[PDB]
Amino acid sequence: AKTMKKIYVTMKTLSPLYTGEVRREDKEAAQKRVNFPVRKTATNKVLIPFKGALRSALEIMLKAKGENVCDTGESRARPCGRCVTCSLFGSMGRAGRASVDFLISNDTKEQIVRESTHLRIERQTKSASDTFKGEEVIEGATFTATITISNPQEKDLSLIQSALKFIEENGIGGWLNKGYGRVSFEVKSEDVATDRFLK
Amino acid sequence: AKTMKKIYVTMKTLSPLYTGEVRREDKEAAQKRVNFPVRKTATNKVLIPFKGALRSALEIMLKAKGENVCDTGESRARPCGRCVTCSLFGSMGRAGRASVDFLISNDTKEQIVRESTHLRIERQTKSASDTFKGEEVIEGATFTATITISNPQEKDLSLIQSALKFIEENGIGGWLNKGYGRVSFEVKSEDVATDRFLK
Amino acid sequence: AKTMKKIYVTMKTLSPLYTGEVRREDKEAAQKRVNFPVRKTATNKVLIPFKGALRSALEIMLKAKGENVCDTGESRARPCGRCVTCSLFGSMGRAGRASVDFLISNDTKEQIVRESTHLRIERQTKSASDTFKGEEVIEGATFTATITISNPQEKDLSLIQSALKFIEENGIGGWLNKGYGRVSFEVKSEDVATDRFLK
Amino acid sequence: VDFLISNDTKEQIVRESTHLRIERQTKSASDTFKGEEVIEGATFTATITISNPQEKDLSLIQSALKFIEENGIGGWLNKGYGRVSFEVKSEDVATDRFLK
Amino acid sequence: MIKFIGSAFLLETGNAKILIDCGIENNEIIEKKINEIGKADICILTHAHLDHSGLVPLLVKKRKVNKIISTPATKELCRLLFNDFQRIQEENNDIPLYSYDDIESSFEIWDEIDDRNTIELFDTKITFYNNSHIIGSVSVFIETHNGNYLFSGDIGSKLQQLMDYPPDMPDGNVDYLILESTYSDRDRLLEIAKTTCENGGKVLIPSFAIGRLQEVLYTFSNYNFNFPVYIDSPMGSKVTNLIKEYNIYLKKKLRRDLFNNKYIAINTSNQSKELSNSKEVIISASGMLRILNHLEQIKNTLIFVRIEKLNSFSAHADQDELIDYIERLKYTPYKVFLVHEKEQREILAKRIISKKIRVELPILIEKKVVLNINTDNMCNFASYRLMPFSGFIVEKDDRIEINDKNWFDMIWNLPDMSHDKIIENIEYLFNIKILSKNRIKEFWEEFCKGQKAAIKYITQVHRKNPNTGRRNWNPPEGDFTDNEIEKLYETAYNTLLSLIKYDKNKVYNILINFNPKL
Amino acid sequence: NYLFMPDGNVDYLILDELIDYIERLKYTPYKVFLEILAKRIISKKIRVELPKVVLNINTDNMCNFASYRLMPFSGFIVEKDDRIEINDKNWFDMIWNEEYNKMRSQIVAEDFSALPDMSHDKIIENIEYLFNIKILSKNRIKEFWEEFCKGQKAAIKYITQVHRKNPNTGRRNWNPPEGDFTDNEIEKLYETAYNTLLSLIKYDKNKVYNILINFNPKL
Amino acid sequence: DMIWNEEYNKMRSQIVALPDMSHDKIIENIEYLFNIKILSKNRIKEFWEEFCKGQ
Ligand SMILES: [Zn+2]
Ligand SMILES: [Zn+2]
Ligand SMILES: [Zn+2]
Ligand SMILES: [Zn+2]
Ligand SMILES: [Zn+2]
């Protein structure tokens, strides 16, 4: 507990990126203008969840490796606590050592957020049968997050970086099947002391 | 769940291509310069939607074959969830196995995107009635897209290759009946592990 | 539909062919060399628009016969959606069943495109008032297009062949009243299944 | 140590929110729930009143505030909630200030 | 509050940062300014001369500006100047400051508001007024809760023959002003150019393309010069067409064939060389630095704006016009921030101190809100202390105040068409598809910018091009004859022009019935 | 600077000879704190005053009308902890909808105002089996007793709410069972929970209270 | 809302048929349109919010 692992990640956006407004008030304010709002801050920066993506990446990969990892993604699934993702990301009984911040943007809305027209086309007519409007995050947009691991082990940085490469393969949030969310990660890791603030 | 299918798709444009700008700010900032802007990134690379083209192609061929597929492209049509296009590209209850990336150009808009004069000519007087300007991707441009299938079945690669042959025959993007968007495809499949990033 | 119609169209040039270059960068690069460059594929082939010579041809012949067809050549003239020209080539809300390819040349710029000189001559002094240097397509050049009809009807090949014969009578491309653009046509038509790629 | 009382009111700072639980094989929302949450940029005011102070108490409180800036305050600290900044205005008063 | 980077003025409104100008006067010095600018919510380009604009794509390149507010004509003149200056930066192949991508991204976040139109951004009310320098010259009035600030802009002159001569001014209270002290011989030109071409020789008038060549052209047009006139200028012809487009933002006398047709636009360089070989007025060059060949045959009356200097054609203000601009504001300002050489600022500051106004050469005034109604009769409904009240929001320049019915009773102690005829005409032209939802939406965006922006827009959509008879409307759906279609287009022109006269609430109530989103 | 002729700068003055004194100051006063003389002082281009934080949260449309400019607004004044604010009709509509939703939340159905049978031993056996596989949990048993003490109808309503297989998702609101089970056993255990709770619905209150203390001692 | 409109209209100037269907039918019809998904939960919720602002 005397040491702590700080993992500063910078996510560069390479494809478009849709994440969804979670706030009912912000949705209802924004669904008079756009049908799929982007999750933004009140300080007008884009918010992306990060803990669930890294967790899901690690459970998919470690279930594929054959390691004992419980599937927390099933409905009302209770984590066992005797896992390896349960130590990083928590269980019913022990909090996760890896506190994972949101991916907040360096820039703001109206600099990385753009407002787009999506379509749905009849197959036998080739005409626009439906139209909606979404909000998307442009390419080259930089997001920063910090993962602080409280009781660090050796496998934590490798597991986080692995999970990040799974996100660079699959996607970070939203419509990952139509091409959205393909991003890249740059990692800067350092091992600080816990008594670095105490003067 | 243990293995995953990579189809690396390299598309060479064989007749001038036009996918329209979708972003309202990008279309509005270009309307004094081009009447038809091409879908581009903020890194100035051409963006083409690909998941919808493959889905529409497979629905058209599988409906003309007689196999049970839903016609999702009708207005507000719920996908059935039991057809193989619902397996590959998703339903309202289950996502698609085949996460289809966008078709990203290898080159910049300065090298591959050109302005153009499209005409409408009167039929009696044989004279220029309307003149408009479009952006078009030149022939010889190379686009890349990676299709990742999460739970690969036996026929998914063959279904994607038949949809690619249909897209070569029909076209991708817009203005398809005028000769625009005729492409060529070079698929490079690869069966990767799901746990390959784990060190 | 269950079947589609493939019309492979081969065009031979009997009189020099000029169709005008459309790209602003290609025109501006051509200005020092020529004043009238030919429309050029960026892989050094010659592209002549086809839809517009088939649509215009069919509109003049069908309007002369008295069939209830509309004029798409007038200024911003909305296609009606009820004539066979609207069904074949497209309306403003239903796309055209006949996807008409561009006329891709079977040879290159260096073989069929020649750079030439035309004059404006005084009627009294019989001297060159003006000289201007254009470039047209040599005779004997072979061009290839493919018209794909998605939901074929009975009188679909006949209307396309009538439009082709009207094109040999009047010309395709530019400078048709001066003598340019007189062509020949050879049609190889076939019925394919829409599910011909599904393996 | 006083409570962190906000400067504003729920209709300006507390926003309902939709959280999800996604199945790892289907990528479908297996579960969801709705939790209220305080926005970013919301300002909270507290007062720490130290009686019989020593020398190190300012440094101790400021270091603990920097730790809370690092690690978060409240709940859901692992998924990214609670990341704040603190501004400190310290002042030494005399205990007989209220006596007129 | 106001930081002075340069022209570069930043206003920190506590809630947001409003940069006004970001101009161009080594690279590390320009970078010092851009780094100091910080994140600005807004850049307000007073005008486009590359001294109040220019380092704005850099602010878009390094992501420091969310949104750029200007005049529409300032936007298009900035477009021409940015492209041309990037072309020059490549002529001397100087590692360019910004790219063309930064130029195209600069208009991505641009926004246009014309004049007398108050845009509320981040607790600041911003309004634009004319100062008669160039086409979209603007003095900016930002009212913040810590004071009202006025950036004069290059106040123009009485010489201007293209703009008004009294630059317009906020009718409210101006606390701080940031004036600028850069500090009719025309007839002489109309004499001597009439002399020289009578002498058979040519005339040369080297002038800048932006806001200088057109005043030299206007004089040569409202007056008669039987000898021929030409423009051998590459941006110059395009900005002359920009005058002919954005003539509605000019003088009221010139609301309605500007510059007549005297000017012949020299389109090509071949025409430039053959014109320089001619025998038979040529306006060209930038500070007499195309121009080189003209110089040879004009050397073989060369006027500066036979060596000749004429000062009448000047655009910047004169000490007296700056003094008259401050002496015409309703309230004398608290402090004149005399910016932009030392000697001019010193002599103007003495006259200002002689006129008893303060100057600093680079007071907690809070615009409070007054309740002025009883709060004793409150109640608890759902955890809130509320009282329904009936009153009026009075907007006194010192302080906003809220008043009851007592106060209101005690203080009481363009073509025109009817609303029903406008409704009927918009409905009938919407059914025959002349007026469409895209047309109504584009009209609403231009009417949000101002009345004159919408007047230009409908003037553009209704102008029948003289070369090819294309009016730029949407054609009618039916079996109408040619004169009936022209009467329908006239009906659409007068209907939208008459709707321009109304207020925004009435226009929104009329149009949200055709396009339910505009 | 407040002056009540000082050559130094005077930002504020607190007062035809008056006009002469005011013009006689170096620079000019920003505001002077003085009727007709105040308006005459206004005529010399100098401002006059003539003698909780208030926040107008409102839209804006301004009719110049008289000499004073106005904006017609019947509305609401809200008193808060350190601020007073001004809101329109839409705020009061929103708080009215939220309060009215809070009202019907209350007095639902018949609080404190057609069932299968199985033996008491069977009921202890089924609740004891579903306690240890985490279906009938302690929160479930608590809200059972809360909906039971308000009557049998509320308990039937809550049980039909938990057991309702939603046709969109196919998910009942029970806690999923812990252990290795196939799907058919999972629905059979859910039906067991259905029948057990609906059968103890028919029993009296002291025969329920005594069956849920040995699972929830803080009932 | 009647008195508010009265005062607002009054003050603003100072400055300047439903089909009759029975309740049981209503219940049957919204049952049928909810089963066939025309009247969905989002539709009923939005119609409820628009009904809360007035008829
Ligand atoms: Zn576990
Ligand atoms: Zn399906
Ligand atoms: Zn038709
Ligand atoms: Zn200027
Ligand atoms: Zn200046």
Image (cartoon, coloured by chain):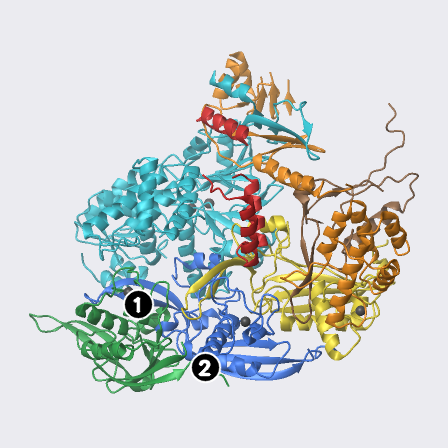
Chain colours: A yellow, B blue, C green, D brown, E cyan, F orange, G red
Mark 2 neighbour density, 10 Å: few (under 14) some (14–19) many (20 or more): many
The residue that disc 1 covers is: C86
Quadrant where the image shows the C terminus of chain B = bottom right
**Residue B157 image point, x, y percent:** 56, 82
Identify the element where label 1 is drawn. Answer: helix
* Chain containing mark 1: C
**Residue B197 image point, x, y percent:** 70, 77
Q: Is mark 2 within 8 Å of ligand 2?
A: no
Above or below, G11 relative to A15: above
Please identify the quarter of the rendering in which residue F117 is found: bottom right
* Chain containing mark 2: C
Q: Is mark 1 within 8 Å of ligand 3?
A: yes
**Residue E475 image point, x, y percent:** 28, 54
In the image, taking residue E366 as reference, residue E448 lies left or right, namely: left
Between marks 1 and 2 in the image, the one whose residue lies nearer the viewer: 2
**Residue E465 image point, x, y percent:** 25, 54
Q: Are marks 1 and 2 on the same chain?
A: yes
> How far separated are the C-alphas under marks 1 and 2?
26 Å
Mark 1 neighbour density, 10 Å: few (under 14) some (14–19) many (20 or more): many
Quadrant where the image shows the N terminus of chain B = bottom right
What's under tag 1, amino acid-wise? Cys
Above or below, E406 relative to F210: above
Please identify the quarter of the rendering in which residue C19 is found: bottom left
In the image, taking residue E231 as reference, residue B193 lies left or right, namely: right
The tag on residue C195 is: 2
